[PDB]
Length: 296
Length: 69
Image 1 (cartoon, rainbow over the protein chains, first blue to last red):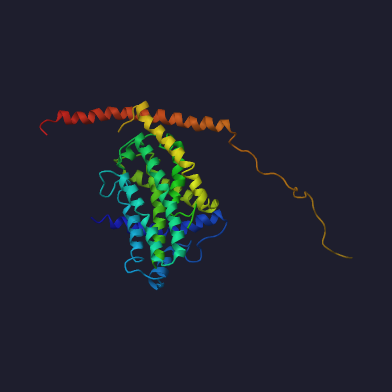
Image 2 (tube, rainbow over the protein chains, first blue to last red):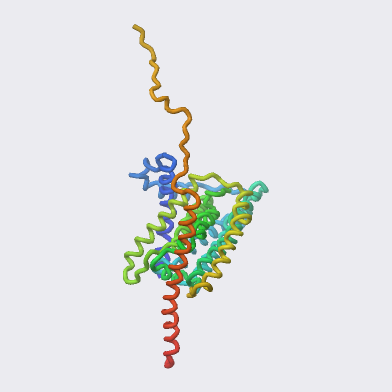
């Protein structure tokens, strides 16, 4: 068992090397030059941010309540890194008995990361804004469970390995046309700062940007696939990375192009408008395997 | 001779011109492609599930065939 370290260390580098992508690709959107001075094309800057924040930068806590504040980043980073384990890939590390149920569970527990940070500060000034940030994540998790089930009820069980085999000739974007549009918006609620925005503070960046890649990959399993090929692992590995990278560009697209939707009208897009739409499509997706034979 | 700043207008840069116009999508035509992709989506998907049934019955047949197990 050495492969676990081969899924944390290159992943922590992927969150680090995001700092290039998150302001150079975002840079050309805004007609500005991103990283250039630090490296040949700014490749030395992502690792330079780590030396700046981890070692030299000291701490000044508000109150430091015994166990908390030095426990919230462990829940933030821990839950973000454990999400990589059930991922199907070409081959998964320790494949669970049911796949997507583990995926929804560790994301619903990832709400605590922003909850314990609100309890860390003694002031009332911070906790009201902290609970508002919880409301952005907690509300969209209702619909996230519904849109997941509609894709599953079309084909395959909860296992993530079966979701690759069902996409043999055509993608799941075409049968789930309005549902694919939902996953572009619903994923951005989890601290992406595109439709709505709120030492150890630096550790939250390493956890929040990790979930951004996680939602990009998870959308490329439920809706993308193209080919499987069990005999050739070479063809799948390259083709999967390009599909995930194109979704990473769309995540940074919303951050630059579109203003914030307001907190009150975030509950008018969802609940008032999205929840009647998602359930109507869920009603449609119950009838689909009954109308025409479609059972795994 | 006196030399000062000379006046030039030429094309006048066009004073207030509309650039925003309807492109690609018309209205009713987008629904023909939109709902058309859905109807093509279900028909292609359900044929694969019927091909899955060929594998499904054959998979469970292996358990019935194996009695020394």
